[PDB]
Amino acid sequence: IEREKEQAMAALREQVASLSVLIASKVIEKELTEQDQRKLIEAYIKDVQEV
Amino acid sequence: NQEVIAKRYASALFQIALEQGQLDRIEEDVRAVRQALAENGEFLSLLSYPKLSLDQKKALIAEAFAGVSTPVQNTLLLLLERHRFGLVPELAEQFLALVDDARGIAKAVAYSARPLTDEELRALSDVFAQKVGKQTLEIENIIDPELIGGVRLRIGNRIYDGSVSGQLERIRRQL
Amino acid sequence: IRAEEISALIKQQIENYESQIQVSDVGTVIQVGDGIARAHGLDNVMSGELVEFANGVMGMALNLEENNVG
Amino acid sequence: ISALIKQQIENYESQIQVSDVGTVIQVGDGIARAHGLDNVMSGELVEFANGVMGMALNLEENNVGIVILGPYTGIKEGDEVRRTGRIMEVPVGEALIGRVVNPLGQPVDGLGPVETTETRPIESPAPGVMDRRSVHE
Image 1 (cartoon, rainbow over the protein chains, first blue to last red):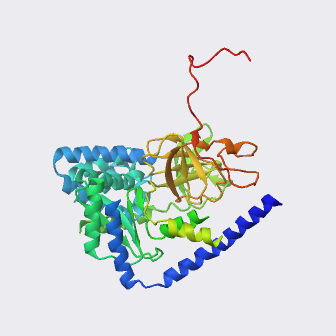
Image 2 (image 1 turned 90 degrees about the horizontal axis):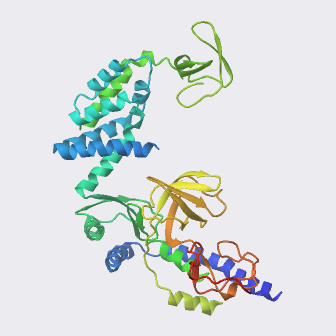
């Protein structure tokens, strides 16, 4: 029961983690794409150059 | 087994094109032949038909491909006599793949959610051509919006995913 | 460029020999031997189908492979 | 659980990564062939798209004979097979003691993860002739 209990807790974090990722993406998706896309390309190019 | 047999033919045509010194006239013609054979598929079923004699099929190629280069015409007439005309578009595609290693150019496909401007395309092309070793780099863009505000670049078989891979690695490292 | 002209030439070459592509119901033999035939052609054969030759000798189509009929 | 999740979100930094990918051509009864993967090694963990692992035994002239280490019914022609970069190895330590584990090193009895620090490759050379000693105990 003690082990199971640790598992129920972990499983519980995971079910919730799953929901959390889907919303984080939806909020992210909702955010601007004009200026932010210009930053992301600029940043992408800069990043590749570090890598 | 078919791709390596196409690669043998494409390497032979590549060696004769590098030896004869007429590389562009071979390359553009094989590109045109590959486009024409990808356009229509009934020509293979025409040339596989048994009641047509081999001289009629050879004259059919010599009439239909009268404008092509001479080593390309000799290569395709050898392909006809070996019953290997069902293997010609793969060897044409692998010939165009192998000739760009002689030119040094690589072909890259970039999946971006927004259509990128040409200056950033040229900058990333020069940067990863200096990285990969190419003299210049060709970039093919796509209009797939599934990426989360970024571009992912494919250099041959090695990709550069940085659009949704941040959130994917975040939810992978969280759990 | 030249690819459109080559496509038009091969399309005219297909349209010139379109009467000899009667292939969809008849066939021509490739291999003959030991009680076996392989026939190019015969697009609309059923499997296990009774099939007559030019002699009136009957035959049975067992293997319906991609480019020939056993 | 929220404080540890916030600490993990603050500690993690986003970056780009390579994959050295290849595409499947044949999927059949536990074994997949694949184009690409031009720098794959003989005998390494090669990872499919749905998270199932696989070992690369046959390296051939234009395809890799990948032997699928799990349920293969979710793998189709055209899936992406990324390269991990490490020879077949199992997580080996003191934490394995008293515990039921599949041959990939994963706990199968369902009692939590196995907390081992260092790994050992599964196909390693044997002890030599001078390394032995006559069996006496």
